[PDB]
Image 1 (tube, rainbow, N blue to C red):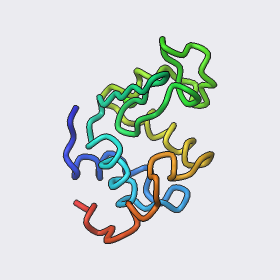
Image 2: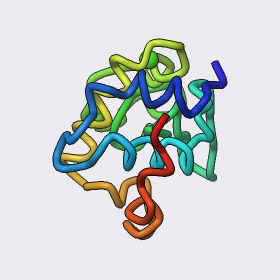
Image 3: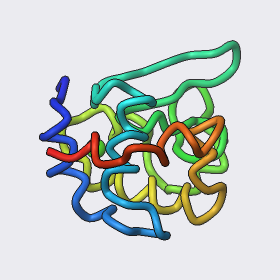
Image 4: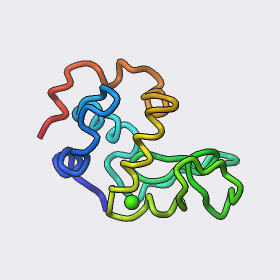
Length: 120
Ligand SMILES: [Ca+2]
């Protein structure tokens, strides 16, 4: 589903302040990662990223391309292509705990300035 900013702000409520990352920061992160598209899928030469949070099949989730993924999130990647972000959020928390926000953002600044712009 292609979501609006406001739908993302609502749907991501359970990430609010997780690991110190504010809800606006998470909305900014989703914008820059997928454009709020829950079906986003992006391939590079050897791996694929899925969903709103572009979760990868190298270490985070298992899929056909990489059946021996480390699968830290213990889930099939295609569960990140549906319209229920409950599991996406569970795994995004695990990603934050392990790699931090730089999983998504080349530089933290991208989502630390004028954060009130990401509110509904
Ligand atoms: Ca999902």
